[PDB]
Image (cartoon, rainbow, N blue to C red; front, side):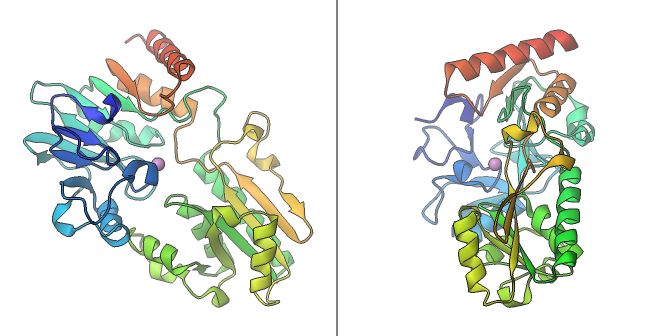
Length: 341
Ligand code: NI
């Protein structure tokens, strides 16, 4: 049945609650972003109002064939009225079109649902600074202090310099990047840009990127694999077998593959610095796992919450085990005592 942490008290609203059939008493279904665990259940046969960002609304229409009459896109940073309740969508710094949702309840409670986010100090200067938040529904994906990772900027720097060096040493090397959902486009776009290539991809993936309002996208991507030296493939194909296979398909145009797997966290982060990352190599194929995250590190999450000073926190991730729940509540208490709210 729909879990309580997907329901917004004092409204008829749910968030990211599309897989439970008809939720009893729900008058509006919000969707924070176009990732499958969140949209699971939507299709062309959905007949209730869906509230989301413009970009998420492009993907509902074009990829899932949801009917236009039921898509209600809202502009960001703008006070809007939904079934008599004031709401605002804010940028979540996750994947394209991902938002956080501020709800202003008739009784005077203010609720922030983060969706999926990577907390950033820039959020401290949005509409959030302007009033108090009583309840926070928080993306707790990496809520544990072992989860450190570099800035997105440092990771992109590493990837650009790596690719550029490899291709300039060997002009017959191909670069490949894995993907399984929207998000992390900076990885492959930044590499293509330094190499003066377009990124080549399947028709299904090109269609997906064409929904995302990226400026100058027609200049950066293509479905012609032959004219491109940066190829995107499913994440599943990023391994020695899948890459040898792909290399055979290119018909002796290339003699080396350099491949990137943008993982979330991996346990080499406890020890290793970004400077010090090394590939796994077999023959003429090298594979780099890089820690490009679109979720908050532990410290970024702690700073955001200690800044917001909410009265109650409701976790949305890692809630399935008692040991996880109990550990998270312990960190919430430390943060509160240390900051004095
Ligand atoms: Ni997500």
